[PDB]
Amino acid sequence: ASPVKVGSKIDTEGALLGNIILQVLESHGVPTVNKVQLGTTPVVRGAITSGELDIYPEYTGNGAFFFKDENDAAWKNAQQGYEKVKKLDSEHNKLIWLTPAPANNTWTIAVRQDVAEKNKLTSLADLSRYLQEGGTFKLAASAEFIERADALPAFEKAYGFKLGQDQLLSLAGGDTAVTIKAAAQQTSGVNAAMAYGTDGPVAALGLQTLSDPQGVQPIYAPAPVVRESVLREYPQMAQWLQPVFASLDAKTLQQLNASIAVEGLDAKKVAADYLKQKGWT
Image (cartoon, rainbow, N blue to C red; front, side, top):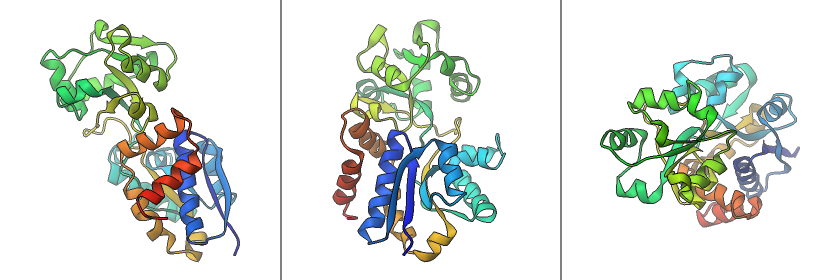
């Protein structure tokens, strides 16, 4: 009878996933309070652990910070990271991690679709092979992404490639909308961009993210996290949200995020349309 307080983070994907959770619950007649786009990670995390939120989408790899377990190898594996934060949040905070999306919202490289399809580039390993075969390549990226040891140099080391100076366009202070745009219109001959794994502009501006099978970056997979006492009152909501989040792979999230961020569709309507199309509402 007491309404379920549904939240999310302020960003595009937060708006999308928060509205998805809210509308799934509403379609089952569950009483709700709309607190979508409440704040940043620490604000929503503080809110759910204080009871100001009952459920919101959180990202698996953030378990590294929640449990002071930075540099644990588990966060570099999608399944191991999920299971780890799920176990820890249950026992320590009575927070239940539901089904995670198969997507990984983390740093990667996105390549122009034409170049990716022509050269069969799916993963960062494919990219490395293409480069060592003399493939034409120029990456737009932030100075930070280029220099930080855990960013481009980590990809380079793990996948065995090296970008020369003429294969880089350094853009001072991000952000990925700008680097993606550079590849999209081939600025200074750029054909690839620094991007996040579920970036809306990747879909809208005609790029394709590369996968990270080696697990160089920690995995940030979004999942509903719900207070145990609330799940206790509506146990069925795990079942409701399972096929929904199972369907959210990277390309799907890129398209939905693009609808909102690039083309200015209402996040509420984008969520509603998706749920209706897939037949969950």
